[PDB]
RNA sequence: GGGAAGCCUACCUCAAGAUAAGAUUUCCCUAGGACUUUAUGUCCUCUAAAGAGCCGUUCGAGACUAGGACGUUGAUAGGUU
RNA sequence: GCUAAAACUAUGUGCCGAAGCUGCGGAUGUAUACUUUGUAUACGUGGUAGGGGAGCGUUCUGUAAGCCGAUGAAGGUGUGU
RNA sequence: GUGAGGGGAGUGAAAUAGAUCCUGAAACCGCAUGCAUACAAGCAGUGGGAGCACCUUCGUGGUGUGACUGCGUACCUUUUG
């Protein structure tokens, strides 16, 4: 099964009208004060005022 | 004497594409599709130059009918009365007066009805 | 006045890079950098490279402060493609297109 | 370009009220359609709505002649297989009088967006009262 | 005040100071033209309807110039019959300016 | 007037995108400037309410969704007894 | 949608209605006269297969050791006529 | 990233002549501005036609858009069609 007519650019863009991306949830940490992904350990090993690597 | 076709062919295709401005999709981009669209537009225009006169005469007749029925006659009786009273004003002017000046149209209706009587 | 950076010949499809471009179009540079830093898309790395290059150009060649910059203009164009051959079943061959793209970023205040 | 079209911003719609007691359905619907479309005004334009608002009261007293009370049929089709439904004039007039007038005038109006707009100016009420006293309708004997 | 005149097989309703285009005339530019066959004169409430024509009425106009309307393409095509032809057209006209109306 | 497993109701489910978009109870928001295109007009400063969502622990709900419960004023899941 | 019709039969007075006919403006073929003409009148001007007539553009040779050109050629892209 | 690629500086008559580099058309793919578009059925135009935006010799002007409306079943070939 294949198309009988080539699809127009208009209909192609209409189909793609649902492809937009979305933003993550970011938050400024307390103890250190940089941005991190919410509910995740910061890239330097801190989470809720505890250190993972001394 | 070898002849290259590029410049003349390009000019012809470009003129057709320029006459195709404003059409939807490939009808303003693709030469094969755009060429068919211009010929059909020409045919439609040729036929509609005749259709326009009919449409406008129908509009004038409708407005004259409304005015005559406001003044107590029908269109056919008003036309007959004016013809018997020898008035030769045409339907375009009669419709213009009907739409823009009610008193003059009432006077014309009185003339026609007097001729009918 | 706008300050421009171009990344040409990036090894990714324009259709894929345009999603990240649309994500960051119109925002302030700090917010856009946060988004690009915490995105998981491949095109995020390339767009971040281009944006940081644009910020560096604005700072060093025009003497502008970064606190007021925003992403005023961004778009992605198609690049030159590479052509390859993939063998199918029963001796048939198909043609493969490997696509690239150009990224343009302009910042201004 | 001396022949002018009416402008929608300058059209003026007047309100009228019509009693349907003892009238014949079709011979009333023709006049209602005329006045809804605006054929009675000298500014009539085919692509502009210039008509009036018509309120119809005492809708269930409308009449038909002959044996049409038992015999005239109203059909509709749900688009499921075998879904053709049928009723007649006596049941329909006792149940929903507004539908009879809506069908009769819908049949006589143009079939497009302008026709949909023109049918919205007809208000049909079963009893002798209407809620549009604020528009001060005039009595129309048609 | 307005009047009804006939020129070039058609009729026009005119007021003083109006410029209008009619079919091509033979009058030279700058000349004056008199219509002595007025069909109607209206002066607010004074209404004169000529039986064929109002007796004594006159409308005076002045010729501005001559010209041609915009180009029109004529296309004829019979499908599947190997036939096609085309031609252009521009219609001549004369411009007039009404200067006087007397009932 | 009577008159059938037939028609309309009656029984179950869905149903106001019924654009004619219906009804009821309760809750929220009442600040100052400048300008002309004197208008539900346009730009400043100050204000972010009732709520909804992102996120997390998840489900007798689930393709993805949607829907249900909870988020320290806590038994939502795991563990422990 | 229509029932002393918006049906049928008979008669009448009006009107609508085509690229038909008339009005106004313009073009063209043939013929007859002006006894060069490009001016009149008359009759014409839907067309497949076909037949006849008249033209537009393109490359190259002569005219050209001429004429236009860095005060901007060809080519590309708009606008006006 | 001692990468690719770019932004300055410099050379040049010219760097949108910057190395697969004279000119750089079309299909095809982006970004920005103006207008229209989420109650309405079909070769997508054509004859009308309101409103809006910009320009303006301020109009019976120009440019872009086209709510609503009459008519309207592509092209070629082969065929009695």
Image (spheres, coloured by chain):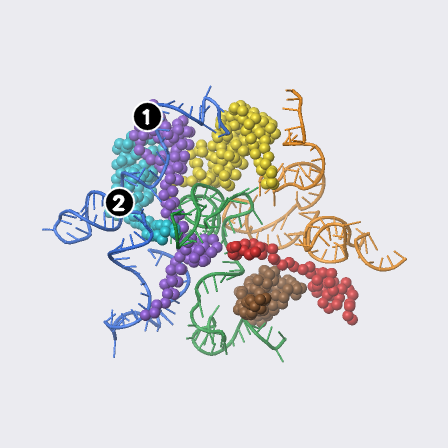
Chain colours: A red, B purple, C brown, D yellow, E cyan, F orange, G blue, H green
Q: Nearer the viewer, residue F56 or G21?
A: G21
**Which dot marks residue D142?**
none
Q: Position of residue C9 (x, y in %)?
A: 56, 70
Q: Position of residue C29 (x, y in %)?
A: 61, 64
User: Which residue corresponds to the image point at 37% horizontal and 65% vertical from the top-left?
Assistant: B5
Asked whether the viewer can see residue D12, the reply is: no
Q: Position of residue D126 (x, y in %)?
A: 59, 28
Asked whether the viewer can see residue B49, the reply is: yes
User: Which residue corresponds to the image point at 48% horizontal and 40% vertical from the top-left?
Assistant: D9
Which mark lies nearer to you, 1 or 2? 1
Q: Determine the secondary structure under disc 2.
A: loop
Q: Nearer the viewer, residue F34 or C14?
A: C14
Q: Position of residue E33 (x, y in %)?
A: 26, 42
Q: Is residue D74 left or right of residue B80?
A: right
Q: Which residue is mark 1?
A: B115
Q: Do labels 1 and 2 touch, CB within 8 Å?
A: no
The quadrant holding residue F16 is: top right
User: Which residue corresponds to the image point at 39% horizontal and 40% vertical from the top-left?
Assistant: B55
The quadrant holding residue G74 is: bottom left
Q: Is residue H55 left or right of residue C84?
A: left
Q: Is residue F69 left or right of residue F46?
A: right
**Which dot marks residue E25?**
2
Read off the chain for label 1: B
Q: Determine the secondary structure under disc 1.
A: helix
């Amino acid at each position: 099964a294949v198309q009988q007519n080539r699809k127009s650019r208009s209909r192609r863009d209409m189909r793609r009208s649902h492809d937009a991306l979305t933003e993550n949830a970011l938050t400024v940490d307390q103890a250190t004060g940089e941005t991190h992904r919410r509910h995740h350990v910061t890239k330097d090993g801190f989470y809720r005022g505890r250190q993972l690597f001394a | 004497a070898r002849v290259k076709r590029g410049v003349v062919a390009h000019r012809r295709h470009k003129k057709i594409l320029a006459r195709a401005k404003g059409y939807y999709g490939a009808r303003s981009r693709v030469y094969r599709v755009a060429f068919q669209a211009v010929i059909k537009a020409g045919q439609y225009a040729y036929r509609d130059r005749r259709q326009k006169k009919r449409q406008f005469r129908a509009l004038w007749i409708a407005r004259i009918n409304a005015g005559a029925r406001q003044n107590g006659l029908s269109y056919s009786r008003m036309i007959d009365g004016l013809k018997k009273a020898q008035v030769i004003i045409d339907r375009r002017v009669l419709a213009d007066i009907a739409m823009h000046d009610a008193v003059a149209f009432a006077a014309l209706a009185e003339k026609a009805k007097g001729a009918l009587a | 006045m706008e300050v421009t950076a171009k990344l040409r010949g990036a090894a990714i499809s324009a259709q894929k890079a345009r999603l990240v471009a649309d994500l960051i179009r119109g925002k302030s540079v700090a917010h856009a950098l946060n988004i690009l830093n915490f995105s998981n898309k491949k095109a995020a790395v390339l767009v971040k490279k281009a944006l940081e290059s644009a910020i560096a150009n604005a700072e060093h060649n025009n003497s502008l402060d970064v606190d007021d910059l925003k992403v005023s203009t961004i778009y992605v164009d198609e690049g030159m493609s590479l052509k390859r051959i993939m063998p199918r079943a029963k001796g048939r061959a198909d043609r493969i297109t490997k696509r690239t793209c150009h990224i343009t970023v302009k910042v201004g205040v | 370009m001396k022949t002018l079209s009416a402008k929608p911003a300058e059209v003026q719609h007047d309100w009228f009220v019509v009693d349907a007691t003892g009238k014949t359905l079709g011979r009333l619907a023709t006049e209602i359609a005329r006045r809804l479309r605006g054929k009675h005004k000298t500014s009539y334009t085919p692509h502009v709505d210039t008509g009036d608002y018509i309120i119809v009261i005492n809708a269930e007293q409308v009449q038909v002649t002959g044996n049409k009370a038992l015999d005239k049929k109203y059909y509709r089709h749900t688009e499921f297989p075998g879904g053709l439904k049928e009723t007649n004039f006596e049941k329909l007039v006792a149940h929903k009088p507004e539908e009879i007038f809506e069908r009769a005038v819908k049949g006589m109006l143009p079939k497009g967006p302008l026709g949909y707009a023109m049918i919205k100016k007809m208000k049909v009420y079963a009893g002798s009262e209407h809620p549009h006293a604020a528009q001060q309708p005039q009595v129309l004997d048609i | 005040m307005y009047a009804v005149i006939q020129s070039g097989g058609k009729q026009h309703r005119v007021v003083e100071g109006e410029t209008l285009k009619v079919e091509l005339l033979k009058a030279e530019s700058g000349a004056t033209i008199t219509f002595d066959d007025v069909l109607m004169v209206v002066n607010g409430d004074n209404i004169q309807i000529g039986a064929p024509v109002v007796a004594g009425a006159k409308v005076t106009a002045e010729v501005i110039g001559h010209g041609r309307h915009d180009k029109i393409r004529i296309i004829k095509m019979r499908r599947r019959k190997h036939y096609r032809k085309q031609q252009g057209h521009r219609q001549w006209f004369t411009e007039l300016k009404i200067t006087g109306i007397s009932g």
